[PDB]
Length: 314
Length: 314
Ligand code: DMA
Ligand code: DMA
Ligand SMILES: [Ca+2]
Ligand SMILES: [Ca+2]
Ligand SMILES: [Ca+2]
Ligand SMILES: [Ca+2]
Ligand SMILES: [Ca+2]
Ligand SMILES: [Ca+2]
Image 1 (tube, helix red, strand yellow):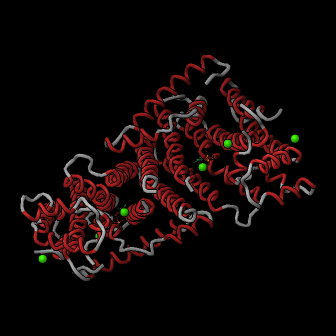
Image 2 (cartoon, each protein chain N blue to C red; image 1 turned 30 degrees about the vertical axis):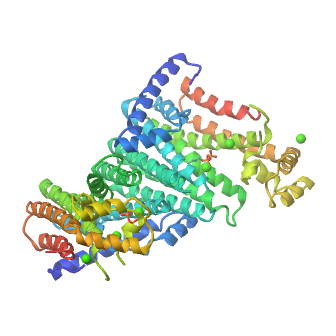
Image 3 (cartoon, rainbow over the protein chains, first blue to last red; image 1 turned 180 degrees about the vertical axis):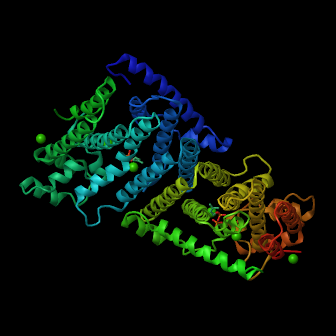
């Protein structure tokens, strides 16, 4: 990406190239018929936020951007891609679709095999950390799939994001810093910062989905997914809260009902409630950066979080 | 199981209990809603052939049946269960079935997370070995899914079994022996023996599916899966080979066509061709046991293979 420091920008950009090379090698490893399938399902790329965060984190150690830092970053990104493959097959909830599903399940699995190969060269602490991280991630997908049962819907939603999204970003910071040989306190801070940042990104995304116009809103609503601002509004002891409770159980479908709900939400206190929750995570993020030495990298991380927050408020 | 040595029988049976305990702990670890799902999909158990083979293999090391041997065995069995979960979802090729599929995909994934936790305590060599093994296994499932393309159907079939089945049994022998501290030659022999045995079990199973009566035959045929004896028969320059080629492309369905094919196969040389291939693997198996010290455990392994072979010939 682009930071204040142009010296930083260049170092990082060079490392991102090394990450992309090793990643491509792994995605294209194996028997022809299998590689063909993986390459056809290749997502067409991404922002690579997770490996970049791992690279930034490594700047706090004695060996920034070293070969094992690049390898850890690739492990994190491979894991990310594997989960997308498995998540996509489940978003699907005749025989040319049952084939498509087998294929993506196996693509996700071969990716995990590749990731494990690299982790074997990174050490058992990485494997242990990965096992916990991937377990959490899978727990988040299961949690989302089963729903809130009879728990508080806001706690459920928070848990789903912490697990499905937060932990892997926390892991990028952890592994980036650890394989750079950073101090334990700094490793821990970057891990915690990643977790807080994961919460910020998702809640901000959810706010935008409901309250913004153009770069149509209400995507989550149509699918029947009620995110933080909606959950807060449904809680209110007001006429708007009451009307939202009475509508948001029945048939979700026609555009007119969706647009009425969207207006109700704009009349509710849900946006600001979600935004205050974003601010609380930003306070957490800032407290973690507090544990790190002042530097342009620290400020680049702070800005990553702050810029996201500013998409929805100040 | 039951071997000649009753002293062996007791040692092994005690270790299998320890394997079952740790396995159950892992399958039942995690959040309530996730454990509930895993336990509901628990296969209802199995023969545990793979962990038993790992335990037998460890008898050739300085530390037979030690705690890490038990842990390796559980890793192999967890991996086995994970692949079944993913394989089952693909054998499936409306919304209460799309839910069932997400669930099994995630169950297989949480199992891999559990396996990785244990491997982190077993060392990087185990993780490396696992990465290769699981990669092969996934390659076999993909290979079966895509079909033989334009390769020799017999080579394809052999590759599918070596990868889908053989490698994990080879891995049980490898890991059992290695974590017992066996000598490299012995570790290697037990690994190779496991691979040969995997081929024997599957080909014998396929022969039985076609040529036996009661403990109905032709399961694979109905599903359109042509195993070794069928592939050999389809190769023959005889009237029976010609008639099989002309039938085994068209509509596979009615019982009368199935039963006619079954009779044709009994008139062909396919059974004996498959059986000679079994004998060739048995020769390989015996050559591997040759590398191991004489002992009741060696003979128990030999008998495991020999007893299987005798289900279909002498
Ligand atoms: C593993 C993982 C988080 C996949 C995508 O999750 P998501 O459902 O938040 O993404 P999308 O909404 O695009 O399906
Ligand atoms: C991972 C794995 C080998 C699952 C079962 O394979 P299979 O298709 O041979 O078993 P089944 O024939 O019972 O589906
Ligand atoms: Ca999804
Ligand atoms: Ca969104
Ligand atoms: Ca309004
Ligand atoms: Ca199957
Ligand atoms: Ca069978
Ligand atoms: Ca006959």
